[PDB]
Length: 358
Ligand SMILES: O=C(CCCCCCC(=O)Nc1ccccc1)NO
Ligand SMILES: [Zn+2]
Image (cartoon, rainbow, N blue to C red; front, side, top):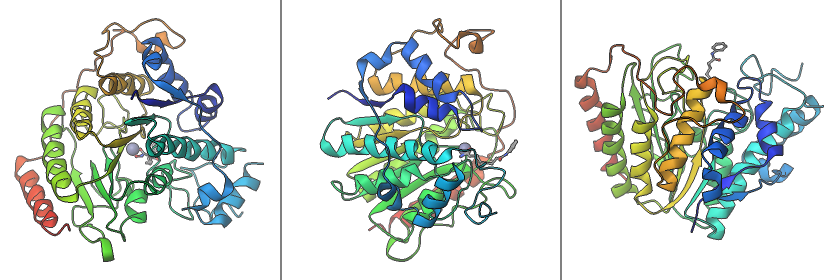
């Protein structure tokens, strides 16, 4: 009845080797270890995602190319600047999926109410192509696995970016719903998913997308979140939840767009949690490394329902939390360019869309 925490040194170190965020998992796990919160969770070692296990969603050519490469044909398979070809990513990606699959497996074995995989949450990678630092849509692998025991699954995406890859995969079906809350403005990755984009075919209206602009703090974010999800849950009536809790919305992230504190996102986490559903907790974006570790450290708190010591404790990465050495984050002071006009104009458009589900 206690939460499953996906950890191993071998995993964490694989996850530190992803170029675009060196030492982030180390840091994350470390601040958590430091607050001793891992001792209040069942630590589960993640399995290696088998060639087939990954092939559930990723077209086998890809998963074969990415293996040779990890030991010319790189530009085909979506690799680029965003996604280097570091020998060897094949194991890196195969550890994130495996972790997310392991977490989902616990949930479906009845091992826990909640499973955590901070290292996962790569909501961009497509079936045949890498995109957005994402090599492997581990959420998709998480949801697919969850779909063996549970009927209706709900993906909620609270990362700064659009969960496009998760949206894509389940845009056709009505058996999975995606709520993504993100920035929308052209040029800004991935530049898919305006409110209008709602899912196609047998699963039309089964894709929510909330476009938001810079400046938004907790107060207003919880509003849009508590709103949407309330109407989504009542309508969709899901059997399990998959949460992507990207850190790049938070103040101090060099991506400097939203203005969240972990408290605000944690209020949303508190909300989703009260549903007493099976819940898969994934990370995502996080580019202020300390703020990220602060953030997911915090969140593990609310999952465990344990309020945390404000003073950061000493450990490996203590120095990173200076100068003020605390868990809380101060919002930056800059305009909330979300006119309260357009917000209500967005709720309705969504609210009316939910009158169709299902
Ligand atoms: O945050 C993410 C993945 C990030 C992918 C967005 C692309 C941003 C990017 O590549 N910008 C950049 C590249 C090099 C240096 C500075 C910014 N998931 O939501
Ligand atoms: Zn992001």
